[PDB]
Amino acid sequence: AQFQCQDDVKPTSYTTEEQKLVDQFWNESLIYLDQYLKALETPTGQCKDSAQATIQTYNSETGKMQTQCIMKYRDVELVAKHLKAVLAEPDKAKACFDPQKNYKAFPLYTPSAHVQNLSATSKWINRPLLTDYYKKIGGEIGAAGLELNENFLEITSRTDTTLHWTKDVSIKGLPTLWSSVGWIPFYAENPNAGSDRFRGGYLYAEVMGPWGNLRIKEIDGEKVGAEIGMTAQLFNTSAPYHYHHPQEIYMTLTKPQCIDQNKHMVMHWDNNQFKQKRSDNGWTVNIDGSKGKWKKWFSNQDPEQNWLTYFERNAIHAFHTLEGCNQTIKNSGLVTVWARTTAQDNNQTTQLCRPMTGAKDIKTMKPEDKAICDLDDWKP
Ligand SMILES: [Zn+2]
View 1 (cartoon, rainbow, N blue to C red):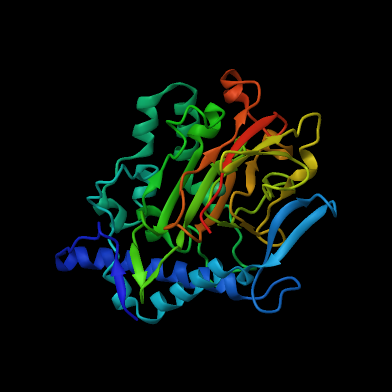
View 2: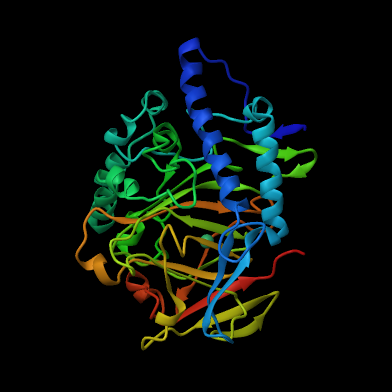
């Protein structure tokens, strides 16, 4: 196959010792992506040819979760095709791989010196530390960011990968990968993103994609939509309802300490539980989960049974860690393998629903608060 890299992949020359640091990073990236392919393709549940994914946590007509065999989606099928191509000719794919040591698009971080010390590669890349970032920010956002990043290894180690993976894709099994990828405090500076603790207690990283370490633009003239990485959300946080054009996949790694520690919601934009009104080339979606109505929309997440979920375009979704033992545990959270399938078409912006009661209530947003989501049509 023919690989065309993204335009910001620049030729590089490493010393012999530096090349070994890159190579270990690359090798663990390939394990991660091979395990990702196997997680998509290995049959589970009542699916014969691929993994069974939750696509609605509450189907309005059945009052029950709704699933689909994940490789029935053509965009997922193409991710798998492109992963197979990468794994079949990794020397060619490696031309598009870079440790992002001098990446200019935006800042990338390592959680802490403790996490940095997990690999010679991470020490060499020498990303700025999130413990320094959040000490400077201070306040309640900084307090949450310190709590997450000071305890990052413990939070991301409380995982069980034995049932749906054949190798430990967590930070324990792939420490060079998890310590060297670029971590992004995606919500820390977003005043619309809800509570201060959620904003400081959220991180993601991208192994493969238009902003990852592996940045392939096209394979055999096909645009690579795959965008694959990981997320970490501190316990006792709730996110605002989210939506966006790209389809999205989460695989839950955290082993919960109570069945309701980590709850998620995904419901299609046109679900009859919401109120929709046509807007100019879009939809206004009003969400009223008040007075306990939200509870039936949210499902428990775990690495065995409810481990896989796939979000169709503009599906409303949220991750919620306030219930149950979130009020007794410590140094815990929700850690996942994360992906989007169409990162090179339509609007990649992560959209946030907003409180119906105005900006005054952003800092307490939670599933029970009435919200408005301004969805845009995507291109066919
Ligand atoms: Zn999302």
